[PDB]
């Protein structure tokens, strides 16, 4: 039937070897495209086409989401997320006042050398102290002198590593959307597009801009199924015949 | 006669091998273009042209519709559509509450091992139970914990397969529009443009964007008729000569 | 005299073989351009230009109209319009109600197999019936079931054929426009740009879009005259001296 | 001295061979530009620039006017305007009523075959009538059938011919503008830019569109003076020292 | 120290050979840019980057002013302005009324042949009259008809010549800007970017458009210093330590 | 015949799917308006009109009543009214 489509799709990815399944229900774009290589074989006295050679049926996929998820980066890199891993990160402390005896007390847990910044953008790298007391020289600051300390601390959280030699596995993807009825303006059917053998593409970009909500985007390349030699399947199951 | 054209065309595709007929009457763009290869011969004292060599007349077609139709994808792929085929698709159930004896009961028809998602984005893959009752570990949820289950179900619907080695067959296209009369502002004639031997082009793209109405588009390449050596026929039939 | 030009040109084309004359007085753009190939001959100490070599003087024409005319397509293809020719076109009837005995009566004159479309976009290709009575199967429709029939009919009208190995002949073109007087704001003369020997160009494009008035456009390539070696003759004839 | 320039330039062209002088006082743009070719000669350990080779100093000019002059086209083509030359142009008149005895009387001075157009866009090419009476066939028109006649007439006017093997000779150009005073707001100086040996470029384009005032444009290439080796001279003459 | 820059730079150029000093304090843009050539050397098993080769550090400069100055053109051309030089320019006289005895008297000082223009754009070139009386033929003008005269006059003023075999020599450029304090909103320091050894680039363009203020622009290429090998020296001297 | 109108209208809405009928007889304004899209074709020497392109006939209605009625909100929302429901 001639139907009207006016929405995007819910996307499901499944890994082949393991079966780990990812779904996105807050997508903003789901697209796929097909390209093909054509050539004409000419000849004869009139120099007219005698044959058409066609090959290289290629399909590409693109998905753009509305929220952020680390598993997308996992899929792109073909890696695994290790939960509850200890990490070394940076931290900043503003407003340390140098006391009368020129000593500053830190209220954090440094792991490496602490670097101090005065109001004129000058640095002083002092090693870590036990009690958390640092003797700031007279040439650096005086009484009632707000300063800054930049030190490394310890945290725990999920860690994903990007290596220079590990690539992606093979996946199975499906888009799902709905199709309306022009005459009656009610939902007519559900449309499923299934790709049974795809390869994630390693090209991606993440740009953080102030005041801009980040929308990550991923791409895939579809390949022919090993057994059935299928690249995609389009299904338009109705909501009355199920 | 000099007439005014201000409308689109109703398109009638038709396969040649069997005569299967497709028609669209809600089009949004119907266009065709012609290209040719030219060269100049030069010689003598002065480098003046002596001949113009012309060859390789080519014609292309483009159609853009307002509704969706699986038959267009079938036409591009040169494949048939199976009716009432059983397919395995994905489904989602939200809001399962884990009871006092950590039992979760599904109200669907699982076919493959279910996957459970807690509120912190963690997965648990468990095989399908007989009574649809699953024992969620206490490390996953305890009580009053909305969970999500993603499982595969079965449905009946139409099916079109895109294969890596199957290509398109030949068709016969024809547009149809009306031409107005500048003096009297009444329909003067009907204009039919008939292409008797075309080949659908495998290049196509389907992009689903939220809030945007999908308008599919197809392309064709016109070839000379086998016997008459025609490539296109333009006909203007008045409404008084019938 | 220094004059102001603010209008388009009335265009006259004339075939050289037989004198067949076409004119357009509702033009929308008339332009012509000249190109030339130049190079520098250098040498000596300092690498200074010693000569300039010029050749390859070319002129092109472009005309864009406001109405539609099959004669322009005839000029581009170098063919002839064969008026009052019988043609085979498509037609469609909506609303055929299947009666109690499952018979549908057509109100047109089919020439080929009729194709029936039910409410769910399914096809049934039946042959031609003498009495115009068709027996629709029970699996296709029932009582009070509006159906659609697509069949081929016969018409008569002007036929133009586009051939894969037929090109255009030579022509003679002339523009005409008026020039004003910047002091008196009154018409002063008429400019008659004349091209003695042009050749139509095969490039062409027709694009039908809903809500858009079609404006066809044709292009020409000017060539040197056979004897006088002219390529354009700009004439500014005053209307007080004729 | 630091001044402000906010206008175009009055332009003067002079031919070298005979001294024919053209001037434009209603220009809309007068520009000139210089280009040069530079290369770096490197070597040694570290690959550092050892020398710079620069040559091929080129200068180009562009002038865009607000009115139309045939002398500009003559200058570009390097030709001469012939005054009071007899020419054969096209003319057309609408509304010839076919009388009771199917005779149409022309009110012009045809020179070649007259072509008649009925209201249905059909042509009839009749020869020249001595008295100017033409017997239109009854199959072509009847009583009260307004027709159209297209025929060639004779006029006199200025003729400029464009040949395929004739080019432009050398010229001498000068721009003049005025420069204000930032402090006193009054005119301070006259700026003269003189080019003593230029060659008009053969590239030009003339496009006529409805409702658009035509502004012709011309280009030149400046060349070194044959004895002084000057490409341009900039003169800044005050209005108090003259 | 983190500061805010929100202005342009006062620019100073100095010639190296003699110390001729030019400055501009009315600028609209002062920019410099750096480019470098990079390449990766790979090898081994896995095709991993083994080394990075970097070379060809290049720095470019661009300055855009708000007023006009012949000194900038001299700097680009590497020439000198010869002040108080006698020159021969063009002049125009409108409104010459031909008297009863067809004599026209000029009010200027011609040096070459005077060219007369009638109201219909026709020219007549006559030699220089001793008393400034010219006998216009009766075929050109009769009485109470205003004509136009174009003749060359003599003036004195500055003169910059552009030759085909003269280029620019080395200079020394310096910008100056001020920086603000984000906390106090008061001027904090002055920034003096210094280039010790640059080379003017002979690629400029001067375009005069009606109603458009002219802003000239110049470019430079910075080169390494002979001894210290420096290419630029950014300095951020403060306004309280100086 | 040339007649004088000096009053409002009684309005009768009616659904098509089921035939549910709503009527108002205390209206205060009943209006309808028509709009259309026009354009001109131009060409030749003189830039004279050659055709008027017309399309997109559109009609809108507005009704303003004097009393309150929940069925009007139901009509706007395309929703049904449940009777005797317990609410907090």
Image: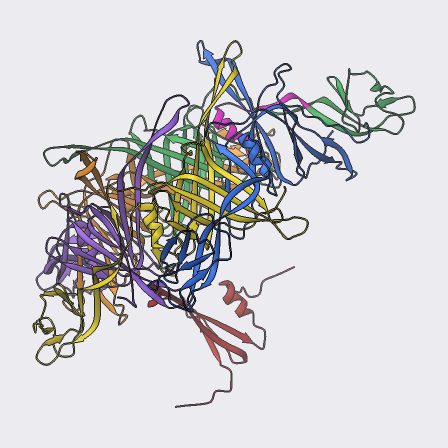
Chain colours: A green, B orange, C purple, D yellow, E blue, F red
Q: Nearer the viewer, residue C119 or C217?
A: C217
Specify the quadrant that holds the N terminus of chain B: bottom left
Left or right: residue E162 compared with residue D125:
right
Residue located 60% across and 37% down the image: E83
Q: Nearer the viewer, residue A77 or A178?
A: A77
Residue D217 in view in this figure: yes
Specify the quadrant that holds the C terminus of chain B: bottom left
Residue furthest to the front in view is E130
Q: Is residue B48 above or below residue E231?
A: below
Quadrant hosting residue A236: top left
Q: Is residue D69 above or below residue E31?
A: below
Residue located 44% across and 56% down the image: E149
Q: Nearer the viewer, residue C145 or B195?
A: B195
Q: How many marks?
A: 0
Left or right: residue A235 compared with residue B114:
left
Indicate whether residue D42 is drawn in magenta: no
Q: Which residues are magenta?
A: A68-89
Residue B21 in view in this figure: no
Q: Position of residue B75 (x, y in %)?
A: 25, 43
Q: Nearer the viewer, residue D115 or B218?
A: D115
Q: Position of residue E143 (x, y in %)?
A: 40, 68
Left or right: residue A128 compared with residue C130:
right
Q: Position of residue A47 (x, y in %)?
A: 14, 35
Quadrant hosting residue A133: top right
Q: Position of residue A76 (x, y in %)?
A: 48, 27
Indicate whether residue A79 is drawn in magenta: yes
């Amino acid at each position: 039937m001639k139907t009207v489509i006016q929405d995007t799709a819910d996307v499901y990815f499944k890994r082949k070897s393991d079966g780990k399944l990812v779904f996105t229900a807050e997508a903003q774009t789901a697209s796929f495209s097909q390209a093909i290589s054509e050539e004409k074989l000419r000849g004869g006295i009139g120099n007219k086409p005698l044959y058409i050679l066609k090959s290289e049926k290629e399909i590409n996929l693109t998905v753009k989401n509305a929220f952020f998820d680390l598993e997308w980066l996992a899929m792109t890199q073909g890696e695994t997320i290790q939960e509850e891993t200890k990490v070394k990160v940076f931290d900043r402390e503003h407003g340390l006042i140098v006391d009368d005896t020129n000593k500053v007390t830190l209220k954090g847990k440094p792991v490496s050398d602490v670097t101090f910044y005065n109001k004129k953008g000058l640095t002083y790298k002092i090693a870590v102290s036990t009690d958390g007391t640092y003797t700031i020289p007279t040439a650096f600051a005086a009484a009632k002198d707000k300063l800054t300390a930049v030190y490394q601390i310890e945290k725990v959280g999920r860690r994903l590593a990007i290596k220079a030699s590990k690539f992606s596995e093979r996946y199975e993807v499906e888009y799902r959307t709905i199709a309306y009825n022009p005459d009656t303006e009610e939902v007519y059917s559900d449309i499923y597009i299934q790709f049974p053998n795809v390869s994630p593409s390693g090209e991606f970009e993440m740009s953080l801009e102030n005041g801009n909500a980040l929308a990550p985007e991923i791409k895939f390349e579809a390949l022919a199924d090993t057994d059935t030699d299928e690249m995609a399947v389009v299904i338009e199951a109705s909501r009355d015949e199920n």
